[PDB]
RNA sequence: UGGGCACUCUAAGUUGACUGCCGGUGACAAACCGGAGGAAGGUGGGGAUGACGUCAAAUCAUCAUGCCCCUUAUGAUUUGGGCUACACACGUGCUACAAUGGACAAUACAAAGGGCAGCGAAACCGCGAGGUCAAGCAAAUCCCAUAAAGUUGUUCUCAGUUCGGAUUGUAGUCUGCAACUCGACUACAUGAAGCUGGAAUCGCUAGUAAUCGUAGAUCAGCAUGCUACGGUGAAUACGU
C-alpha cells in the first residue's frame, strides 16, 4: 500500500580500486518483478547489498 | 445550549409542585409531561414520572443528573434488535 | 522527554509539539509564548536552555494520561446515570443527532452484508 | 491629436485613446504589466501594432471596466484597432484580414432547468 | 528500432483484395 | 420638484411622461427630458406538473420600468398643474416637492 | 459526424520561443482551466533543462517530440468470430497530437518531486530515444508489425 | 382536513413562531408566495387568464 | 470634486441579414461549394413555442366532482411522542486521497439579484462564532459586498505526513414559549477509513466540458438540494 519501495539518488560505490557504480538511479514500485542482468563481476550481488 | 445570560429553563409548574413540599415528610412520584425543563440541584432526591409518549415512566433524580434535562432519562423509541 | 511522549527529532519544534495527545497546533505554537523559542528551529539543535523551560508549561496543562481517562470518566458518567447518550455509547452508534439509517460506519464497524 | 475607440469582449468594456509617442501602455493608474499577470496577453493586445507595422509609435492610455484579465486584455485589443482605422481608415484592408474588427460575440450561456448547467445533464441510470 | 518503413511496404500488400483474387485467372 | 415614473408596461410610461412634461412647457418653465433609469426584471420558476415532475418547469416574470423627470424653474403656475390627473390608471408617479 | 467535417482551432505563438508547439503543449499541461500554473511548469523546464544540456532550449525540446511521432498505428474491424486489428498510416497532423500527450502523461508517471523537472527529465531522456514516451512509439509499432498480415482489410 | 384547519389559521395562535402561511385561495400549505399569497398551481392558473398585473412569461 | 454630456451606461424609437450581389458545378429546377462589401453569413448564439395519436401512464391529497360509505365519529381541541427509528441492499450528490498540493503573509480584476415594524455601516468589545451602541437608505444614491480562483513572496520535501476532517469530550454564541429526543454556526482536545477504484457504467461538439466563487425563492431558525449569475477555460470528430 504505497508506490515506491526503494530508490537510488546518484549513488556511487567502489571496492578500494574498483569503481562499481557511478551515479545511477534505481527504483522498484509496489507489486513488480525485477530481473537484474550483466555478467560475472558486474555488481549484482553488491547492488543487493546496498539495499 | 440556552445561554449564560438567560438562565436554565424550567417549565414554571415543575418548580411550584416541587417547591410546594419544600419541607415535607415523604416523596411521592410527580406526574409530568415537561420533558424539556433542565434539572436544578433542588430536585435532588425526587423521582418524577415523565412522559415518553404513552406511559409515564419513572426515574428518581440523583446528584449526577444535576445538569441534564428531564427527558434525557426516558426513552421514546423502542428497538430490541433486528 | 517533554512528557511521557517523546516527540520525535528531525522536526520543527512546533510541529512535533503536536505529537502529544492533548495539544495540536493552537496550543503548540503559543506554548512558545511562556518560554521563548522561535518555533522554526529543529528539535535536534537546541540545548536544555529551553528544553526544561518548555518542560515547565507542558505540565501547566493536563497531558497524556492526565487527560485520557479524564475523558473516559466523562464518557462513563453517561453510562451510569443512563441518559440518552451513552446508551448510544453502550450500544455503539452515533450519539448526537447523526442519523443511523445510511452512513454510520465510524461508530459501527465494516459492513455485514446480509440476505435480501 | 489623439484617436478614439471602444472595443468590447465578454462583459468587459474598455475605452482606449491612441496618442503620438513611444511604446508604453497605462491602464487604470497602473502599468499594464502590473495590471496583466501573464506575458500571453501583452503579446497579442498589441497584435494591431504588428499587422499595420507601426510597432512603436503610440502611447496607449486605456480605461477598463468589467470582466477579468483575459476579457480586459482583449477588449483592449479591439480598441487599439478600432482607434487606428479612425486615424488612417485606409489601413482598414489589412487590419481586417487578420480578423481584428470582429467584436467576437461568444458570451456565456443561460442555464437551462432540469440540467445542471448550460449543457450538462444529470447522471442517467435506467435501473 | 523497428525501422518503420513498413509504410512503404504495406501498400503493395494492400491491393491484393479478397475479390481481386476472385478475378484475374492465371 | 423631483418626480418619478413607474409602470409594468412601457407603453403608458412614455405616453404619460413625454405627454405632460410639455404641460410644464405650456407655461414658462423648462424641464429635463425624461431620463430612463435601470429597470428591473423579477422572475419566478414554478412546477408545471400538479404532481411528481420536477425537471419540467415553467418561468414567468414581471418588470418595473422607471423614468426620471425634473424641471429647473417652477413658477406659482407650474405646480398648480400638479393635480392634472390624466395618467392611464396603471402608472404611479412620485412627487416629493 | 455524419453530416460532414469541421475546422480545428488555430492558436497564436508563444511570447518567447515563437512556436505554436509550445502553446499546444500548455493545453496538454493545463488542467481544470488554469493557464497560470501551467506556464511555471513550461518555462521552468526549458531552463531547468537548458542548464543540463548546452545547446538551445528549443532544439533539444523539438527533437524530444520527434522521436515520439508514431508513424503507423492500429485501428479495428470485426469478422464474426474475430475482430482484427488493421494497421493504418497516420496523418501528418495526428502525429503532433499524440507526441504531445505521450510526453505529458508520461510525466505524471515519474518519480521526481515537482513537475518542473519530471517534464524536465523527460524532454532530455526522450531526446536520446529512451524512456516511457518513446517506447510507446515502439509499443505501437510492433502492433502495426505483428498485424502486417491483416493489411488488406483496409479502408 | 380542510375547512377545519384553515379556520384555525385565520385565528391568531399563541406564539408567533406559529403563523404558517397557507394560501388564501384554496388552502394549501405547501408552496406559497408572500408577494401574492398564491401557491404554485394558482399563480399559473391565474397568471394565465391575466388577472395578476404585470406578469408574462420569460424567454431570456 | 465646482463645472460639464464628450467618452460608457441606462432604454424608447429606429437601422441591420434577404441567397440582394458577384464566380461555376446543376437545365430535372430547386439547391450546393467558394468570394467581396459587414459587427455577425447561409433557420447568427440560445430560449419560449410540443401535431394525430400511444401508454385504461400519474393525480379523487392542492382544487371540482358522479356513485358508494361514516355521522356521541372515519368528525373536533390540546400536551407529548412519531415521519430523525438501523444486522443491512440500491438510485442522486459532497468531501478527499496532495507538490499543477498544505499552511501563513502582500495584491488585483465580474456580473445577476434581495432590502420596513427589513437591509444594518463606521466606532468599541471578543482568539472566534457574535454582542452594545447606531449613520444612511422604500434604494442606478445607502447597505448586504471581501468575490474565491489569480499574482509576488518565506516555507515545508514523500511520509497515512503540517496530507484528509469522520467520530467524540469539553466550554460557548445566536433564534425561538422550547433546540431533550431532533437546529446552524465557533474555541480547544480527539485524529477514523482513505495512496486514484472489481465486474460494468455516465455527461458533454465552444466561451460548452472541467474548477471557482456570488446571488434568490421557501424561511422565526436551518442546504452539500433546486432555480439563476458571471471569472479562468481545454481536447478531439478520420469516417459511418
Ligand atoms: N571485499 C571486496 N574487496 C574488493 N573487491 C571486491 C570485494 N567484493 C567484491 N569485489 C569485486 O567486486 C566485483 C563484483 O562483485 P559482485 O559480488 O558484485 O560479483 P557478482 O556480480 O555477484 O558476480 P556473480 O554475478 O557471478 O555472482 C568483483 O569483480 C570483485 O572483484
Ligand atoms: Zn392553491
Image (cartoon, grey):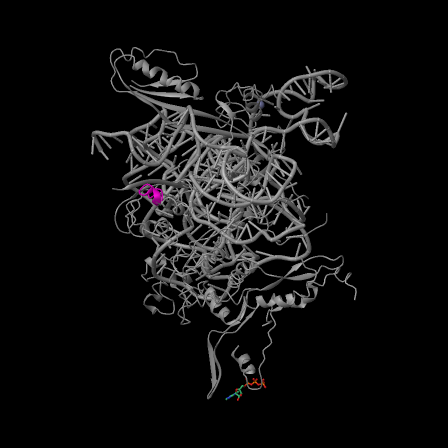
> Residue I199 versus residue I54: which sits nearer the camera?
I54
Picture quadrant of residue C6: bottom left
- In the rendered structure, does residue D49 fall within the stretch colored magenta? no
Q: Can you say which quadrant of the picture contains the C terminus of chain G?
A: bottom right
Question: Which residue occupies 32% across, 57% down?
Answer: C33
In the rendered view, does I58 fall on the left or right side of F73?
Answer: right
Picture quadrant of residue E3: bottom right
> Residue B12 versus residue I202: which sits nearer the camera?
I202
Q: Position of residue C76 (x, y in %)?
A: 53, 51
Q: Position of residue G113 (x, y in %)?
A: 46, 65
Question: Which residue occupies 41% across, 40% down?
Answer: D11
> Residue I181 versus residue E18: which sits nearer the camera?
E18
Question: Is residue A47 shown to the viewer in this render?
Answer: yes
* Above-or-below relation of I29 to C25: above
* Above-or-below relation of I58 to D80: above
In the rendered view, does B15 fall on the left or right side of I123?
Answer: right
Question: Which residue occupies 57% across, 66% down?
Answer: G137
Q: Which residues are magenta?
A: D80-90
Q: Position of residue C81 (x, y in %)?
A: 55, 45
Main SS, magenta region, reads loop
Q: Position of residue G152 (x, y in %)?
A: 70, 62
Indicate the quadrant of ligand 1 in the picture: bottom right
Task: Give the farthest residue toward the bottom.
Answer: A17
> Residue I210 versus residue G56: which sits nearer the camera?
G56
Question: Is residue B37 shown to the viewer in this render?
Answer: no
Amino acid at each position: 500500500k504505497s508506490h515506491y519501495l526503494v530508490r537510488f539518488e546518484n549513488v556511487s560505490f567502489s571496492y578500494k580500486s574498483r569503481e562499481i557504480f557511478k551515479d545511477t538511479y534505481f527504483e522498484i514500485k509496489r507489486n513488480q518483478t525485477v530481473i537484474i542482468e550483466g555478467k560475472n563481476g558486474s555488481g549484482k550481488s553488491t547492488l543487493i547489498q546496498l539495499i | 445550549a440556552r445561554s449564560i445570560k438567560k438562565g436554565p429553563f424550567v417549565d414554571e409548574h415543575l418548580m411550584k409542585k416541587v417547591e410546594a413540599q419544600e419541607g415535607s415528610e415523604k416523596k411521592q412520584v410527580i406526574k409530568t409531561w415537561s420533558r424539556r425543563s433542565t434539572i436544578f440541584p433542588n430536585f435532588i432526591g425526587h423521582t418524577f414520572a415523565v412522559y415518553d409518549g404513552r406511559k409515564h415512566v419513572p426515574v428518581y433524580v440523583t446528584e449526577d443528573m444535576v445538569g441534564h434535562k428531564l427527558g434525557e432519562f426516558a426513552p421514546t423509541r423502542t428497538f430490541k434488535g433486528h | 522527554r517533554i512528557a511521557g511522549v517523546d516527540i520525535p527529532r528531525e522536526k520543527r519544534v512546533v510541529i512535533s509539539l503536536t505529537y502529544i495527545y492533548g495539544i495540536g497546533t493552537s496550543t503548540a505554537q503559543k506554548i512558545l509564548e511562556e518560554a521563548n523559542v522561535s518555533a522554526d528551529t529543529r528539535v535536534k539543535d537546541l540545548t536544555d536552555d529551553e528544553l526544561g523551560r518548555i518542560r515547565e508549561v507542558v505540565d501547566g496543562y493536563k497531558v497524556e494520561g492526565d487527560l485520557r481517562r479524564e475523558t473516559n470518566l466523562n464518557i462513563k458518567r453517561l453510562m451510569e446515570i443512563s441518559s440518552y447518550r451513552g446508551i448510544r455509547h453502550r450500544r455503539g452508534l452515533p450519539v448526537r443527532g447523526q442519523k443511523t439509517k445510511n452512513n454510520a460506519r465510524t461508530r459501527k464497524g465494516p459492513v455485514k452484508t446480509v440476505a435480501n | 491629436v489623439e484617436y478614439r475607440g471602444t472595443g468590447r469582449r465578454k462583459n468587459s468594456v474598455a475605452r482606449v485613446r491612441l496618442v503620438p509617442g513611444e511604446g508604453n501602455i497605462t491602464v487604470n493608474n497602473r502599468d499594464v504589466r502590473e495590471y496583466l499577470p501573464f506575458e500571453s496577453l501583452i503579446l497579442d493586445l498589441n497584435q494591431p501594432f504588428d499587422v499595420t507595422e507601426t510597432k512603436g509609435n503610440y502611447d496607449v492610455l486605456v480605461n477598463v471596466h468589467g470582466g477579468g484579465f483575459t476579457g480586459q486584455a482583449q477588449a483592449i485589443r479591439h480598441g487599439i484597432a478600432r482607434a487606428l482605422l479612425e486615424a488612417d481608415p485606409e489601413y482598414r484592408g489589412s487590419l481586417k484580414r487578420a480578423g481584428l474588427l470582429t467584436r467576437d460575440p461568444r458570451m456565456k450561456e443561460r442555464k437551462k432547468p432540469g440540467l445542471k448547467a448550460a449543457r450538462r445533464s444529470p447522471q442517467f441510470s435506467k435501473r | 528500432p523497428i525501422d518503420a518503413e513498413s509504410m512503404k511496404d504495406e501498400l503493395k500488400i494492400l491491393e491484393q483484395y479478397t475479390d481481386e483474387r476472385n478475378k484475374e485467372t492465371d | 420638484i423631483r418626480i418619478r415614473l413607474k409602470a409594468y408596461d412601457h407603453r403608458v410610461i412614455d405616453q404619460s411622461a413625454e405627454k405632460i412634461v410639455e404641460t410644464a412647457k405650456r407655461s414658462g418653465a423648462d424641464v429635463s427630458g425624461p431620463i430612463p433609469l435601470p429597470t428591473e426584471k423579477s422572475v419566478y420558476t414554478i412546477i408545471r406538473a400538479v404532481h411528481k415532475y420536477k425537471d419540467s418547469r415553467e418561468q414567468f416574470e414581471q418588470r418595473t420600468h422607471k423614468r426620471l423627470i425634473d424641471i429647473v424653474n417652477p413658477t406659482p403656475k407650474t405646480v398648480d398643474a400638479l393635480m392634472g390627473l390624466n395618467l392611464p390608471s396603471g402608472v404611479d408617479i412620485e412627487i416629493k416637492l | 459526424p455524419r453530416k460532414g467535417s469541421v475546422p480545428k482551432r488555430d492558436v497564436l505563438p508563444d511570447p518567447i520561443h515563437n512556436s505554436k508547439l509550445v502553446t499546444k503543449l500548455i493545453n496538454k499541461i493545463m488542467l481544470d482551466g488554469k493557464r497560470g500554473t501551467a506556464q511555471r511548469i513550461l518555462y521552468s523546464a526549458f531552463d531547468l533543462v537548458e542548464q543540463r544540456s548546452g545547446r538551445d532550449a528549443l532544439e533539444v525540446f523539438e527533437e524530444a517530440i520527434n522521436n515520439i511521432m508514431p508513424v503507423l498505428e492500429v485501428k479495428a474491424r470485426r469478422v464474426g468470430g474475430s475482430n482484427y486489428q488493421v494497421p493504418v498510416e497516420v496523418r501528418p497532423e495526428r502525429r503532433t497530437t499524440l507526441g504531445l500527450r505521450w510526453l505529458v502523461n508520461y510525466a505524471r508517471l515519474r518519480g521526481e518531486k515537482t513537475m518542473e523537472d519530471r517534464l524536465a527529465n523527460e524532454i532530455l531522456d526522450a531526446a536520446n530515444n529512451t524512456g516511457g514516451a518513446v517506447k510507446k512509439r515502439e509499443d505501437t509499432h510492433k502492433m502495426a508489425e505483428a498485424n502486417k498480415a491483416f493489411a488488406h482489410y483496409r479502408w | 382536513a380542510k375547512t377545519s384547519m384553515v379556520a384555525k389559521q385565520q385565528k391568531k395562535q399563541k406564539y408567533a413562531v406559529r403563523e404558517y402561511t397557507r394560501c388564501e385561495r384554496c388552502g394549501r400549505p405547501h408552496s406559497v408566495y408572500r408577494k401574492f399569497k398564491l401557491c404554485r398551481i394558482c399563480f399559473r392558473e391565474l397568471a394565465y387568464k391575466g388577472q395578476i398585473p404585470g406578469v408574462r412569461k420569460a424567454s431570456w
